[PDB]
Image (cartoon, rainbow, N blue to C red):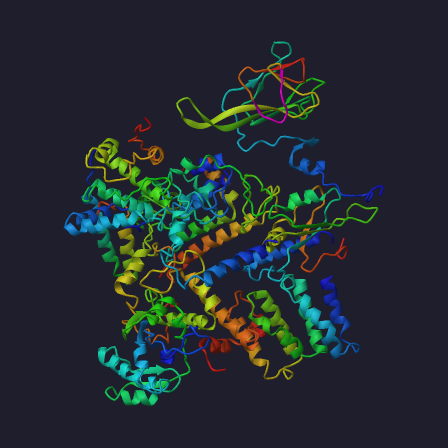
Amino acid sequence: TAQCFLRVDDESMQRFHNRVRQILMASGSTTFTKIVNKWNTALIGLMTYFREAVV
Amino acid sequence: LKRQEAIAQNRRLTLEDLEDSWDRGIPRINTLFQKDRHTLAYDKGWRVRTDFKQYQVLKQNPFWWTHQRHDGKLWNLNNYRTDMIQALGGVEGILEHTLFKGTYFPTWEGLF
Amino acid sequence: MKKIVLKVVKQCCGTDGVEANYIKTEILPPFFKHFWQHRMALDRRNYRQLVDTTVELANKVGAAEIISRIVDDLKDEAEQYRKMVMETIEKIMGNLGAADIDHKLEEQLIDGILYAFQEQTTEDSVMLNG
Amino acid sequence: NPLTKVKLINELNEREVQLGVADKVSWHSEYKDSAWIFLGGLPYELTEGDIICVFSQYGEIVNINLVRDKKTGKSKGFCFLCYEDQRSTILAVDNFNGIKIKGRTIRVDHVSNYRAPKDSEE
Amino acid sequence: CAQQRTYEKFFGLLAGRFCMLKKEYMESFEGIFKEQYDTIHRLETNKLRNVAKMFAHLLYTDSLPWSVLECIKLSEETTTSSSRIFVKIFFQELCEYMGLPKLNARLKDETLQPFFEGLLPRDNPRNTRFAINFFTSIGLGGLTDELRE
Amino acid sequence: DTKLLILALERLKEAYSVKSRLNQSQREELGLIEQAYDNPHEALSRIKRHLLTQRA
Amino acid sequence: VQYDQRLFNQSKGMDSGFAGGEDEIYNVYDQAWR
Amino acid sequence: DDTNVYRVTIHKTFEGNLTTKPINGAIFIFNPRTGQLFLKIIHTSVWAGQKRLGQLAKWKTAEEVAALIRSLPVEEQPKQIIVTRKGMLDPLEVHLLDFPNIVIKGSELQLPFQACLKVEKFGDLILKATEPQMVLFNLYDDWLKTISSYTAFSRLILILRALHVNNDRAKVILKPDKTTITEPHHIWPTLTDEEWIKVEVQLKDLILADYGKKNNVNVASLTQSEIRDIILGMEI
Amino acid sequence: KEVPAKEKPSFELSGALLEDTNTFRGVVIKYSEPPEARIPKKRWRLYPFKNDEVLPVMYIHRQSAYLLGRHRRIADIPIDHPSCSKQHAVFQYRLVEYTRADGTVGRRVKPYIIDLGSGNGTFLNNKRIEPQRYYELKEKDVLKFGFSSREYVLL
Amino acid sequence: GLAQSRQQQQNVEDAMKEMQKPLARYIDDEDLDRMLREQEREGDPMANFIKKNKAKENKNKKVRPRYSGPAPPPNRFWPGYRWDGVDRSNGFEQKRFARLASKKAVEELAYKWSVEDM
């Protein structure tokens, strides 16, 4: 009957940008595999809730 | 349909929950068949307490909308690693890293 | 009754009466046929009594006659049976010695105890002292 | 003494499940090529048909042997059951041990050699 | 496409993008269909579904000639199992895209339609009765007629 | 009754996976959690003791 | 309904697996590699 | 491997007598690092006109081997060649004058490439040929994506030795179920790792059982160094 | 020649093996509930009438099965009737598949009655019933305890 | 009684797989495309078109009849259950089934516990 077009709200991408900003801050107090694992947890926490919205 | 078929007949669900591959459905059917069904069925009122746990212990959770023992693992990324291997070759690090002065390692599959 | 006759074989062969060829002709072949099993190594009162009889049987008969009949059992897929064979070997070789073992037997026992050392699961130290 | 062997055979299986013994060396590779099992502690009100009905759950007994006395008796308490397959004897000695039927408990063991009129322990 | 867990509509889109881009892709690709159904007994119960919906998606979005169905042989003597539940989820899954009416017509209304053996087997009162029974069981029954006089 | 208390204690135990932790407060938190583990009924009635008469 | 015992007890828990908010402890890739 | 350059089939003619037919032969060259199998055809037409046919193949082989060395590029030619039992150290020495830096060595690692004539895709290719085609096949089918060349060699020579000592049960072991399909561009079946090592265990049990049946030796009475010496083919 | 032997085997059922499974505290009960036996989902009550007027009322919505007999020791529903066996007839609910006029299919609660093979037999509608089959009970039908006529009506 | 029959069946299958069939079977094979057309393949509306009802013929390994269709408990070794096998045991099948399921769960949690800080 209809079509549903989807985009990501600006507060969500702002929250993810500030998220990776604090992992850049925490890079100086932890190692490299820890901040890459933290990047990965943030990327699953974005993408598995933003599956069709990331495209 | 298969539950009412097994009630109408007198058989047992031996391996007929395998056509749906044991990990399908948005509640992920293997959540029902686990160790803690009778206790985690009494954990009602969830997915909202985890969102209020941003007003608790300082580790910010990116998983406020789910936890695996009630709605299940909603994604199984397992073959992305294997396709990363097949995209960079199975010798993706052995030519680069000195495995040769690690020991005499001829196999590189028992490495831990 | 297996436990009772396993205790009887120990104390009935140690003084003067039975000789070597008598035992190694008709006493020990059914002893290795019917008693060296997996069910007797499980019960500890049957686990200890087998090796405690086999010590005196090796005192009466000899070293390599018993060992060369149970040296091929060190490559089994059971841990407790290999532990029983290892306790048998350690008690015979600590009581009797190793002069009776020739060049046709020592590589078998060394390879067996190395293969038992490679594939043990529990944190026991009886194989270490063996 | 008449029913502590039930506890002994139960502690064997408990030690097998405790130590983590695989099926290749879990006491049943020593009793191969034999579908005969010995029974112990049966009540005297049991016929051959009831024994077939209670032990045909894991396969029908091909060869039954009750210890029927010569002239003055009816039964003693022992029984021999020869199934089709040896795994049926495995499941029968692992599952039908420790149960009770009308009072006195029964026990299941292996035979592995040949049938005998009286050699076992009452 | 045949192997991704649950089917992803992304493939009947890339696939279609080719399948109407250059003339060749549609021809080759259709060849893959006719080739495909007439085996379809190897992969089953999953890949069978992903591939079935794969083709239903092409038909629905077109970019594929409506006559690929000349190969589908509706028999119930000569259909075999996994073939049968290939075509099941095929129509049943194509059902809602087109809806029943817009399918019912486009299945038939095209005039030139009689290329197939799928529905039109107006032949002996066996595979004719078997069609009706099948499409009633698959739960569409959007086309059923009386050829029994 | 125990089937909810064990849920609450595991809900509290989930937030403690790293062990670079603090000096007194959260270590005695996990100590009280494991004391409630070793004795469910003692903490179960201690909740009731806090639950009838304590409001300051 | 007679459920089989093989389907039962295949996974324990009452935790999450996504443990709290500690984003350093490798939640992904549930099974092994070799 | 140049053992199967000459081989005689078993047949019965229209007469009752028995004779020999010098049918076509094979030359095996194997690379254990990648799995490449260079299979050279020796047609029947060179088996007529020449004399001492059982002694001239050792001189006819090395010319085609040197032509293969000249045909392949610089980075792919070998620095060492491990031949079979010695009849070719001096012919390869006089034929490799254009490439002096290649070492020719005869070792104790004999390999049953004659068991490679027992598989069917090699067998119909070696029997039906009208030209020295010089085919280039692969034995490490899809193993390098998961395992190394080391485990691949340790699997391949065991399966080939099992096919050599008994083609019957080593043929039925490689198809353990009725769902053991083989893609046309490969020669080995496709199956999971647990049944890979299961097939490995039962084929080394086949080899040890054939040894214990041939020489009347207790299998459990052999040390694992001796089991290694049997499983590689050491002269005992 | 008089007999083969004076002893011989049996091959007959003892009471004991059947008894341990089905216990009235002093005796075995015949009638294990069939697999589709379930709680009645309709309102149902068995009313006894001595002569057409109310005596007790037995609520049948509680259990899947109900036993008829001579004393409240054994059977769920007892009668002061000297020519009723201890086990007389059994009331049994079941789920069966059904089809309605429209062709719609599904699971229906049906109650049934079966004689136990009691010493004096049983009757429905003032007509004798055969033993060893579940008869379909219909609303208002009369149950009675012995092959002719009796001092109590059950509805 | 039946283990020797199983040995005869596996030896005749061994003979037909060895003396007539090649070393590797392909996709076509003239046997597998027949078995693929003879699969069950649930989700088929044509099942009730040719079958009346799931009746009970003389479906047994021998000529003698077989036990009816209630549900027996599983016993890890798929048996020839007949002549009144009504679910009496000491509880050894269910206990070790729960043990092996718990082992398969704790190896999954132990891999997690080992992979934490890597």
Magenta segment includes I130: yes
Q: In the image, D80: left or right of H122?
A: right
Q: Residue furthest left?
A: E22
Residue E110, x across and y down, in percent = 19, 35
Above or below, H75 against J18 in this view is below
Q: Residue furthest right?
A: I2
Above or below, D81 against H27 in this view is above
Magenta residues, as a range?
I127-135
Residue I32, by quadrant, is top right
Residue H76, x across and y down, in percent = 25, 77
Which of the two residues, H150 or H59, is positioned nearer the viewer here? Answer: H59
Which of the two residues, J96 or J83, is positioned nearer the viewer here? Answer: J83
Above or below, H123 against B19 in this view is below
Magenta segment includes E67: no
Q: Residue furthest front?
A: H15
Which of the two residues, E3 or B35, is positioned nearer the viewer here? Answer: E3
Residue H190, by quadrant, is bottom left
Principal SS element in the magenta part? loop
Residue B28, by quadrant, is top left
Q: In the image, D38: left or right of H125?
A: right
Q: In the image, A31: left or right of J16?
A: left
Residue I44, x across and y down, in percent = 53, 19
In the rendered image, which quarter contains the N terminus of chain I?
A: top right
- From where the camera sits, is residue A48 visible? yes
- From where the camera sits, is residue C113 visible? no
Above or below, H129 against B77 in this view is below
In the rendered image, which quarter contains the C terminus of chain I?
A: top right
Residue J93, x across and y down, in percent = 56, 49
